[PDB]
Amino acid sequence: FTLIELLIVVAIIGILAAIAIPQFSAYRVKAYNSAASSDLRNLKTALESAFADDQTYPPES
Amino acid sequence: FTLIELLIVVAIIGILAAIAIPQFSAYRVKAYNSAASSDLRNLKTALESAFADDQTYPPES
């Protein structure tokens, strides 16, 4: 509308364009880690189930 | 909160929804089996007790 109105908008667009976007890197690597430790604690039950069938842990591959 | 925040959540919900759920089928069939072998080894003591009363194993049914 008025030149002064178009001077507040550009003064607010500048504000709302920098709101300290956080580093969402550590908060995701923790999920990837806790998939692998879960997966290992599960894998152990398969190994120690298979031993109590065969008196041996499985052959590799 | 922020669109980027709602992009990590959907990136973690996808992770924590696939954590390699193991096949809990063999680990239960072993229990059903070891009920029946226990039950037989017990049933034998009843048969060979009853013989030493009557000089005969029981009639069927």
Image (cartoon, coloured by chain):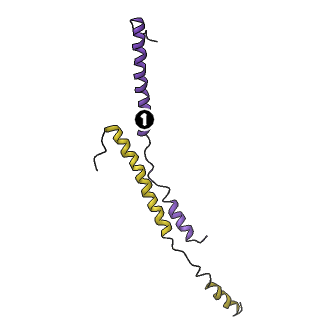
Chain colours: A yellow, B purple
Residue visible at 62% across and 84% down in the picture: A15
Closer to us: B12 or A7: B12
Image quarter (top left, top right, bottom left or bottom right) of the N terminus of chain B? bottom right
Q: Residue furthest bottom?
A: A3
Q: Is residue A13 above or below residue A31?
A: below
- Left or right, A54 with respect to A13, comes to left
Label 1 crowd bin: few (<14), some (14–19), many (20+), radius 10 Å: few
Residue visible at 38% across and 42% down in the picture: A49
Q: What chain does badge 1 belong to? A: B
- Left or right, A60 with respect to A44, comes to left
Residue visible at 48% across and 66% down in the picture: A28
Q: Exactly how many numbered labels are in the figure?
A: 1
Element on which disc 1 rests: helix
Regarding residue B31, the answer to whether it shows in the image is yes
Closer to us: A58 or B13: A58
Regarding residue B57, the answer to whether it shows in the image is no
- Left or right, B58 with respect to B1, comes to left
Residue B41 position within the rendered picture, expressed as x and y whole percent measured from the top left:
40, 22
Q: Is residue A40 above or below residue B42?
A: below
Closer to us: A16 or B39: B39
Residue B32 position within the rendered picture, expressed as x and y whole percent measured from the top left:
44, 32
Q: What kind of residue is marked 1?
A: Val
Q: Residue furthest top?
A: B55
Q: Is residue A5 above or below residue A22?
A: below
Look at mark 1 in the image and give the residue it sits on: B29
- Left or right, B35 with respect to B13, comes to left
Residue B29 position within the rendered picture, expressed as x and y whole percent measured from the top left:
42, 35
Residue A48 position within the rendered picture, expressed as x and y whole percent measured from the top left:
37, 44
